Image: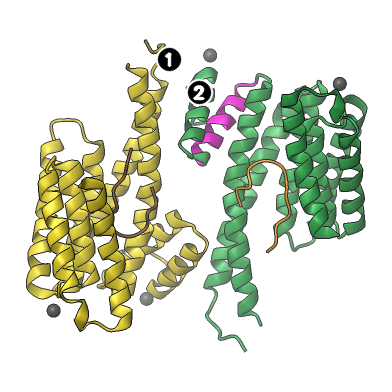
Chain colours: A orange, B brown, C green, D yellow
Amino acid sequence: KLMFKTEGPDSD
Amino acid sequence: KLMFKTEGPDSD
Amino acid sequence: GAMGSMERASLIQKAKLAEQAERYEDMAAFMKGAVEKGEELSCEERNLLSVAYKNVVGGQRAAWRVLSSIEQKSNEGSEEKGPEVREYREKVETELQGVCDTVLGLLDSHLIKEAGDAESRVFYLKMKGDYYRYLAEVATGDDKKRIIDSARSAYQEAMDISKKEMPPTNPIRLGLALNFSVFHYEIANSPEEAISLAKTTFDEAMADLHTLSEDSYKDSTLIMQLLRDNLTLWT
Amino acid sequence: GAMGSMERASLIQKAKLAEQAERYEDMAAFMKGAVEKGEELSCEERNLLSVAYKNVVGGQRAAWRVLSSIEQKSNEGSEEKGPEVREYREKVETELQGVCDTVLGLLDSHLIKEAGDAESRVFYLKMKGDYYRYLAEVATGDDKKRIIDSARSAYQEAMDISKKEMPPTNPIRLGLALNFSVFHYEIANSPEEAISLAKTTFDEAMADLHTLSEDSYKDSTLIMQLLRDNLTLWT
Ligand SMILES: [Ca+2]
Ligand SMILES: [Ca+2]
Ligand SMILES: [Mg+2]
Ligand SMILES: [Mg+2]
C-alpha cells in the first residue's frame, strides 16, 4: 500500500 | 566494528 | 510489571541505549516501565516513549500489510491454500492490537489526565488519535465506526488545544495536523478535508517562520515538507 | 512446544509468509516447530531454517556490538554512569546466547545425526560452526577456548566432507569456506590461515566454473565475490 507521510519514525 | 563478509543474510 | 524493580532513571537510560542499538521492543518496555512509575514525563521522555512504540507498531503495520495483500490475492482463479494466511495475518493483527491497547492504556492510566501544559496534553492526545488510527487500519467489524470516532475525537481535542495555545509553527502542532490530515484522507474517506487541513496548516506555518531562530526554523520546515509531500500526492 | 499442534506443512508455509513480512522471530519459531516434528529437512527447508535464525541472531549481534562499544568507552576520563550499560549489554548477550543454544540444540537433537547426504551434513555442521562462532564473539570466561574449539571442530568436519564429496564451486562448500576463513581471521587470531583458505577456495572454484550452467555460475560467483571482498580487506 502507498503510505502517506505521518509524523516521526517512518518505521513501516 | 568492521564486519567481514560471511554467508547469507547480512543481517547485523 | 517486569520493570517495577528498576529505577526510573535507569529505565530512561536503558531506553536511550536500546534506541542506539535499534532494540525498539526493549525501548518500549523500558519506557512503559518509566511511565508506570507514576510521575509525569518530560519532553525528552515523551519523545522516547513515542519513538519506541512508533517503531514497534510500524514493524507490525508493515507486516500486516504484506500479509493482508497476500490474503486478498488468495480470495481473487487463485488456488486454495487453506487457513494459514488468514491465521498468520490474524496473529500479527492481534499482536498489533495488543501494542495499541498497551499504549492507549498508558495514556488513560494516567498520562492524559495529569497533563496540563499544552505541549504535553496535545502530545498525548495526538498519540491517542494515532493508536486508534492504527486500530482503525485493521478494523473490519461492528466497532470500526466507534474506533474511527475515538481517533477523530482525540485528534480534534488536540487540535482545539493546539490552535489556542501553540504557534502555527510549533512542531507538535504541525505533526498533529499532518497525522490528522492522513486520518481524514485514509481512514475517514474525507480527502477534501485532508487537503484543506494540510494546506491551511502549511500556509499558516509559512507565515510564522519569520519569528523563529535558525534551529526552530529547521524543525518546523522539516514537518512542513511532509505536509507538502502529501499534498503533492493528493493533488 | 507452542508449535506442537500445528501441521508441519503449515509451519513451513507460515515460515515463508513470515519471511515475506520480515518477521524473522516468527519465521525462526515456525522453523523450530517444523524441525521438532522429527522428519529430516529438504534443501529449501534447511535454507528457511538458516535464513530465519541468521536474521534473528544478526540483529542481536549488531545490538551487542553497539552496547559493547558504549561499555568499552565508559571504561576509558569517562564519567561514571552506574551499572546500566553493563546490565543491558548482559541482557542482550544472554538473549543472543539463548538463540545460539536453541539452534545448537536443534542440530544436536537430531538434525546432524540423521543427515547422511553431503549437502545436508555439511550444511548443518557449518551451522554448528557458525553458532559456536557467534558464542565465541561474546565469550570472555574460562570456556572461551572450548567454545572456539567447538566452532573449529564443526567447521573442520564440514570442510573434510565438502572436499571429499562436493565440487569446489558448490555454494554450500563455498559459504562454509568463507565463514571458516572469517573464523580464522576474527576468532582464532590466524589471519594467514584465513587468507590462505580464502585464496585457495577462490582459485579452485575459478578453475571449475567452466563445468557450470549459467544459473549455477551465478550462484557460485556470488559467493566467490564475498571471498574476494574479504581478501581485499585483508591484503
Ligand atoms: Ca526510585
Ligand atoms: Ca501431521
Ligand atoms: Mg503557548
Ligand atoms: Mg557429490
Q: Please give the name of the residue rendered at 11% of the width and 46% of the height, measured from the top-left corner.
A: D192
Please report the bounds of the magenta region as a residue range: C25-38
At label 2, which amino acid type do we have? Gln
**Can you say whether D102 is above or below C6 in the image?**
below
Q: Please give the name of the residue rendered at 60% of the width and 85% of the height, measured from the top-left corner.
A: C78
Q: Toward the viewer: C80 or D86?
A: D86
Q: Is residue D210 left or right of residue C187?
A: left
Q: Please give the name of the residue rendered at 28% of the width and 55% of the height, measured from the top-left corner.
A: D229
User: Is any atom of residue C127 visible in this view?
Assistant: no
Q: Is residue D131 left or right of residue D77?
A: left
Give the letter of the chain under mark 2.
C
Asked if ligand 1 lies within 8 A of label 2, the reply is: no
C-alpha span from label 2 to label 1: 9 Å
Q: Residues within 10 Å of mark 1 (few under 14, many from 20)?
A: few
Q: Is residue C60 left or right of residue C153?
A: left
Taking the image in four quarters, ligand 3 sits in the one at top right
Q: Is residue C158 magenta?
A: no
Which residue is disc 2 drawn over?
C13
Q: Toward the viewer: C101 or D93?
A: D93
**Can you say whether D126 is above or below C207 in the image?**
below
The x and y percentages for residue C193 are: 91, 53
Q: Element at badge 1? A: loop
**Can you say whether C160 is above or below C42 in the image?**
below
Most prominent secondary structure in the magenta stretch? Answer: helix
Q: Please give the name of the residue rendered at 36% of the width and 61% of the height, measured from the top-left corner.
A: D51
Asked whether disc 2 touches disc 1, contact meaning CB atoms under 8 Å apart, the reply is: yes
Instruction: Determine which of the numbered discs, if any, sits on residue C141 in the image.
Output: none
Which residue is disc 1 drawn over?
D81
- Residue furthest bottom in the image: C77
Q: Is residue C77 left or right of residue D157?
A: right
